[PDB]
Amino acid sequence: VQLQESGPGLVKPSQSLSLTCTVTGFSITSDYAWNWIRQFPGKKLEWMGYINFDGGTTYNPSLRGRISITRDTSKNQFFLQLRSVTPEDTATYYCATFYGAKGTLDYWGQGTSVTVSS
Amino acid sequence: VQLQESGPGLVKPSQSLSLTCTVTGFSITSDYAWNWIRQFPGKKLEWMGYINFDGGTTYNPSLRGRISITRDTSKNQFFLQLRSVTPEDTATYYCATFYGAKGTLDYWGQGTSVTVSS
Amino acid sequence: GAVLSFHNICYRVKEILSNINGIMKPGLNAILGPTGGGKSSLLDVLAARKDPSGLSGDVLINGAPRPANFKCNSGYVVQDDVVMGTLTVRENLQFSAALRLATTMTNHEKNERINRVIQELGLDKVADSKVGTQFIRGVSGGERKRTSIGMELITDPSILFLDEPTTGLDSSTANAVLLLLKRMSKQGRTIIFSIHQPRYSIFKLFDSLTLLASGRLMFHGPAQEALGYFESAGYHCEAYNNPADFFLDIINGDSTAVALNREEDFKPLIEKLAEIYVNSSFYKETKAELHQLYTTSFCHQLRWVSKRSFKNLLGNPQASIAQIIVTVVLGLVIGAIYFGLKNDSTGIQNRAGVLFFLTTNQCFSSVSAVELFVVEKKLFIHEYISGYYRVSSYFLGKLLSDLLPMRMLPSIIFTCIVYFMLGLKPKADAFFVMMFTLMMVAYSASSMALAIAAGQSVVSVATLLMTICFVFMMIFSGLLVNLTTIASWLSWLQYFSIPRYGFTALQHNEFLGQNFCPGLNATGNNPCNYATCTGEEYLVKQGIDLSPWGLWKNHVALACMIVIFLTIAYLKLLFLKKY
Amino acid sequence: GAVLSFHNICYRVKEILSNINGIMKPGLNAILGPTGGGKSSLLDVLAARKDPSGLSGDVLINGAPRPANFKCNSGYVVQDDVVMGTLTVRENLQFSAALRLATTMTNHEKNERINRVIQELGLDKVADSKVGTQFIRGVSGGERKRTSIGMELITDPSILFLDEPTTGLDSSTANAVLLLLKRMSKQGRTIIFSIHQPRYSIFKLFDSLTLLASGRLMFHGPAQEALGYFESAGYHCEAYNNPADFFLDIINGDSTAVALNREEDFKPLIEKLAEIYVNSSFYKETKAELHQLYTTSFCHQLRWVSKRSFKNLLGNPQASIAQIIVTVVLGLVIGAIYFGLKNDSTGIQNRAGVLFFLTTNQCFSSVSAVELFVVEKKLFIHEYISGYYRVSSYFLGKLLSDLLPMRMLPSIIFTCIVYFMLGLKPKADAFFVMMFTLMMVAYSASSMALAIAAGQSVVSVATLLMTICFVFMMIFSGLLVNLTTIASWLSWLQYFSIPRYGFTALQHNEFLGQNFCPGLNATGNNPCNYATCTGEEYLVKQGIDLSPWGLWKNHVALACMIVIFLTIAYLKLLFLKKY
Amino acid sequence: VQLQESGGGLVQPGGSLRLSCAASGFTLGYYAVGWFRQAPGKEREGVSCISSSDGSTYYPDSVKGRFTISRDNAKNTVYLQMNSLKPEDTAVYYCATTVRINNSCKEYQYHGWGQGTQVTVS
Amino acid sequence: VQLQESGGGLVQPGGSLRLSCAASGFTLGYYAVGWFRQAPGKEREGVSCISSSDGSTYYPDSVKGRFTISRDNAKNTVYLQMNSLKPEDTAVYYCATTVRINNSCKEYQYHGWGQGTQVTVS
Amino acid sequence: DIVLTQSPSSFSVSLGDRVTISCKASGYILNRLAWYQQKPGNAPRLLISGATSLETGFPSRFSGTGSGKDYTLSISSLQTEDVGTYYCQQYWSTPWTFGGGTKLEIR
Amino acid sequence: DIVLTQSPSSFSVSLGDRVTISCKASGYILNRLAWYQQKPGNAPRLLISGATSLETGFPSRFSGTGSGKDYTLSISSLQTEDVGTYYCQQYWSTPWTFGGGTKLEIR
């Protein structure tokens, strides 16, 4: 029911970027699907991908083979891995929640701004 | 939301029975399905048939061509016709509503005891 | 007159005809030899029946080269009878008279010429009787061969060619046919024919024998002088032996055959016998004599082809009635299983299945449409060379009266039975849209069938290819696989699927304005996701446009496919090998 | 010795053979007459080749009635060659020697008899060469006919029957075959044969001619005195005329045929000539002489039939390789469209479509299994009458090596290609369950195919019925129509559907434990109605039981169908008309 | 296969002369021969018969003196003798044959084969 | 269809005798005839030829006196005259034919057909 | 159709006990069963929807469990305003069939 | 895929007006659109699910209309507590695409 965003904030180009979202008040494997949204330095948003409660992961075809989503059930969180980072991906990263039955992202995260500079 | 029953209580055998349910607080053509449930002189229940919000009517296979339900929008009611009534059809008739998205009968009516006698 | 001559004939396909000379006089000229010889290959050279690319001889009629319309003024009797068994003898040669003649003369003159032919030939007993197909029985073989002979006798040809008139007959009617030919030639008319294994009972009738062996001429001259010729060459004819078989044994070269003569003198087999003939008196006598020397309109030939095709179709109520009955039974059965389509969770599945099966059946029922230009290939080629019609008129006549009425009917029968027994959509326009879509699917499948088999000689190869093509067409329909989940490099293949075009139109016609959830008004909004309660949701999930253009573009595509396939079939017929 | 006799022969099918008498001495006995006469119907009576219900004569060998094993000790050369072209000449007659002979003697003696037969018959040049099918070419017609003759010569028959050895041949090799037969008879061996339109080059070889016309005997005696017999009856033979055709023209009764003699005297046609022969001296001389008078085990004949079938299958790699290749390409293509099955709203549709198409293809691929007992019907009847094997051994041999290995392979190829390219269920047991179900569906379809066509002579009628049956079987599968919405009086028809049994098992294997709604845990409960989010809901909605028995009962039904159809096919083969 | 006969030309009447009816190709032992007589200006009349099983028989009109008959199967032929004057002269003497078993030769047909010889009488 | 010839039996030597080589069925005008001679005890030697286009030619060994030739197409035959003594006597005199156009008859083959006649010389 | 059966036709329990009402089904219901409670002389009010959830206006003493073909309703600490007749109804197929009857009777 | 565009990228309105925001799509959505309101410095808050309904915690001034391909957000009697950016998201297919942005600004 409550989400918390964390991870590094500066990654060197042509490398791997890792984010971690932890969940409090609700279990990962109970009902919902957990997503990753980025807001570019402007007024644009893009959906990366989601991980289902069972483990199925679905990614955005724009990110061709650059995205990996992995969960941990014991401490109730999920990590995003984005490889081969390009300095144009300087967006703010949020972890949202997918209800499924309603089809809309109800609960969001605080978000963090990750800058890719040399 | 609120349902009221009306009709006779003494129908001669081998004849036609006509009952009416009046709906107040909601529209009969808006969302729900409207049912008829008869409770036999005992502790058994039987679902006779229902009418959709558009006009689709579905009946129980037990009543082979004996049941016809017709709705009137102006007075916001639905009526039940049961032909060839028999002495052993002495049940009390409720008119319930069917949500559909939930699958259960939420609101009911008072019911009328119908007696078939000579 | 009407004397045929051929000088220094040489034909190259491998040179199959070496130096051949000969003059065919008005009489009964016969060509003899083994099957592999030039026996048959010379008859098709004397008549304009082979491509002139390889002919290097010089053939003349009365000392002048043959004109362009020589094939139109010289009858040719094909070995295998190409008479239509469904029509009658009188109607068959009436059809021939109506095309091969001119339209200046009234029908009375054509009919009196028809009567004269059937009387001269002796075809009055079975004049108004059917020839006979394989199921129904009619006239016997002799009179069928006689009818085929009379088909090209209508225009009173000056020269008549026959390709083995005895083959396929028996020992009784062969002499009757040969005597008929001799009696016809008695008035005076050049008759050149090929003969296979004759008897002495018919050999005495010949007036000019031409012996061929592996393309080499081995004798030519009077037929009654051949036996003495070969006797003087050192080959004795044993008593009670057929002179024709006596010649053929020498030609083949059987050691166990006739014995040699006694030799009084004071190139394995085939180049010695020919060389003997080159320096013979017959060769010098032949060489001295040798060195001494459209009509109908397009419509007039469209109506007749269409009428003949319609008569053939109605003559054997076994190909049309069978499919009519099976369509009627299939419609009743389908209406029986799918009776009373409900608007519940199982309504979508039943509607999709019943709309898919009808389209698949309409597509698969056109595989049997390759018997249109395959079973009639030989007859078409013969009548095209003879000069009956052109390719366009034949193509349209076999299209208007064979494919058009036998494909429209099953769709009408299916639509008027399964519709109201199911309850698809009680509207006037939906019924006609469904009928129109089924008609287009059937027409497109039949047109592609025609485009595939438009000049093949067998059906065992076109049907397999069409079945394997229709299976792939059925895969990309929309029911067995979701067309929106295809890979981008394979999704284009869906645009070449007739069943997909029909099925999309049927689904767009059926699923527009239907609710499939009892007690759930999803028209306003869907409170629950993953619900597909409304028919529009199913159409969008299947990748189908909801605009009316998303319905009519299917028929536009089907019509375009029809036109392309018909043009391809007509071109394949046009560039066929006509020799 | 080995003198055949037949007295007062009368055969009734319409009495097709009236009073016939004759003694066939050791030599070259020929039967002549028109096609409709008793020419062929008497050869099959002299040998035990017709049902003894209608035979009312009395046939003897050396003055004693023929034993029960007369057909096993008298060769019969069928007109149309039934030699298998795939094997070689040596292997063909080795197979014959392995069956007609006894198993007491070693293989060395069988092989030396084989060598003696091929040396005597003159089959050493092409001893180890293939006979030749239609696609591949082998020996010429003469060598094939000689191989067929030698097939029955293995058991050194005392009497040899031949049904028109000249038909289907040419003039050059006919005399070769006849001379071979005469040379074989010179040692002394009764050779009775039918002959159609002979030549005088072979007529002089006959030693006893029997003329038949419409079941009536017209002459019997020395063949060299028939011409004088008919000359003394008022029929002259013209010079250079075949005596055989001279007899046939009289038999038919052609007025244009040979002319009459001059009559010095001091029942239209057929009963006057028989009556002439009845009061003739030949009849009295014939009547006076007339009035003066298993081995192998079951396994030994199962192994050989199976080996021959396997050699036939591998000798012509165009029927096995073609279907292997098409299965391989179909699997790759299907894996191409259905790549990456997702667990979303479109997952159920794709899974159902791909599981339905595989079963439908597996059922429809067995339509071509009617070429098992149809293309080999004539040959099989000949082997069964001759004494080669019994019905059970032939049925099992043509089953173990023709249907068993050519049906298991396509299922394995489909399962190992489309499974991991799709991602159905990553478990060891599911893969094998799918393979097993596909194998059972293919086996059941093939067994039904054999049950339908088990004694028919053509394939054009079995395949159409097969297709029309499989279409209805496909209708009641579960995808095109919901099996729970059928009327009670039509729902029972679903129990006779092989594709339904296969498809139910495949679906129960695939849809157990799958979620199809992203972000919705329907395993606990379904908060939304009309959702079908879980695979179990789809199975229950389709009418499929969720217990493991609801999976294994499909295979139980398939096995029961296999057994019933195989038994029906074997019974249909057992009660076939063997005459 | 053909059926010929041979005779002669007599000079002085009253002598004895013999005709032979020879047949090659086929054996005459299965047949019954008949000597028929025709003249340039008279009708066709036979002389007598031969039976294939029993002896000979005679059904003539006025020729009943010295005409003997003999069938010799070794040379495959039959013979005709003439000894009496027989004022009937210079006949073709055709020779036919037919195959029957029953008695009473004169009820047969005797289909002829070929032309005949010629005799002379002065 | 057969090719026969006719001759005679001479009594006193020195006379003139004409043999004929007749052919029926086929006309002899297309062919070239050759008279060959064989005796019971000698070898086979021909006499002379006939050409189908030009006149006659002679290639004998010692018989070069009165042997004339004549081909009559009206009767379809050829003739051989003999007038001289010709001490060679009693020969079969076979008669053959062959069909060629070129000159030099003696280079042909002259395939024979049938048996010949016989002559006598005292 | 799907016949719903209730093994206990009548119960004899006391106050403050655990009451277990179990009802099975002929076919597979798939968590589409609802519980109804009827008072002696009133309409049958609806207790539980979805066989697991629980509707408003009722205490938490009522629980619903079960999966497959049989489902159980549990009452904890039975008090004196909980008497009546209990029914289980399936809503999977169209002929909705109710259960039997479990009329509670305290002693 | 389905790309979502908003024709008005910037509005110039005042307090107490009926603000209309239009958002059209490429493919058919079937009332499967959501509206998000992002304040300048927080995460986007959900406004509407289903383009017809309305989430709790918001006044009845926000209304969502439109069917088929284009949808509309309507605000009645706008006050000064509604400035920010508005997005229209589609959740029909799997690759969900957000819209552009309509940044409200008072004068």
Image: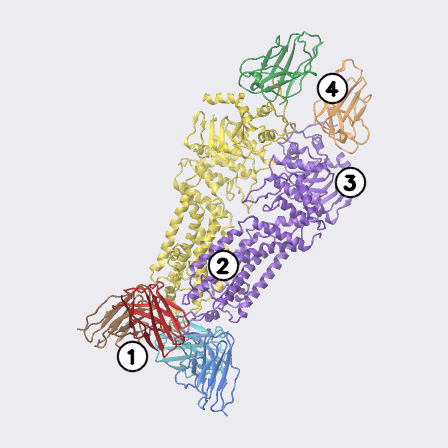
Chain colours: A cyan, B red, C purple, D yellow, E green, F orange, G brown, H blue
Subunit of mark 2?
A: C
**Type of amino acid under label 2:** Phe
Residue under numbered circle 1:
G57
Mark 3 vs 2: CB contact within 8 A: no
Q: Is residue C353 left or right of residue C118?
A: left
Subunit of mark 1?
A: G
Disc number lying in front (3 or 4): 3
Label 2, label 4: how far apart the Cα atoms are: 100 Å
Label 3, label 4: how far apart the Cα atoms are: 45 Å
- The numbered disc on residue F91 is 4
- The numbered disc on residue C414 is 2
Can you say whether C223 is above or below C442 in the image? Answer: above
Residue under numbered circle 3:
C290
Q: Nearer the viewer, residue C133 or C531?
A: C133
Subunit of mark 4?
A: F
Locate the C terminus of chain G by quadrant: bottom left
Q: Is residue E86 left or right of residue C340?
A: right
Quadrant assignment, res C520:
bottom left
* Label 3 element class: helix
Q: Nearer the viewer, residue F74 or H17?
A: H17
Disc number lying in front (2 or 4): 2
Locate the N terminus of chain G by quadrant: bottom left
Query: Which residue sits furthest front?
Result: B118
From the top left corner, tell me how far across and down residue D240 is, in percent: 65, 29
**Type of amino acid under label 3:** Leu
Query: Which residue sits furthest left?
Result: G107
Can you say whether C333 is above or below D25 in the image? Answer: below
**Type of amino acid under label 1:** Gly
